[PDB]
Image (tube, rainbow, N blue to C red; front, side, top):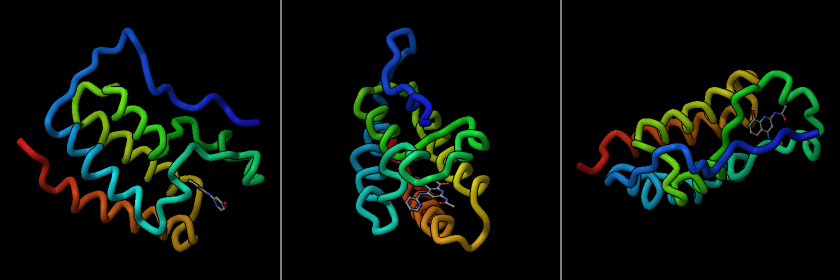
Length: 124
Ligand SMILES: CC(=O)Nc1cc(Nc2ccccn2)c2cccc(O)c2n1
């Protein structure tokens, strides 16, 4: 079945709220959330509902925009680079599990190119 989702709070992890992390929630995430290809990434992969029983045998660092959202809302991150790593992990997983030109990869590559032009400039 499905593994536990990644943690969205951790009381012994130091937390911070920088200007660039506010921008990742308020601006970067909340617009990517609205893209037409955003739905498969708005929650952890449900390997049971999707009949992908091999997903979590291949992917061992799962990540998804729904986890990132709760992490941003809970001030989980020390800095913006930690949150950007989570985004890249989400995109990289999708390219590892699937193959060039799959419908899901096209969705991810569309989000990823949008993600890059949106983080091109972060606040100060
Ligand atoms: C062969 C295959 O179904 N691959 C998939 C399917 C996903 N979500 C879905 C969900 C519903 C229908 C089809 N697809 C998916 C999601 C996130 C990351 C991934 O790597 C994914 N890979």
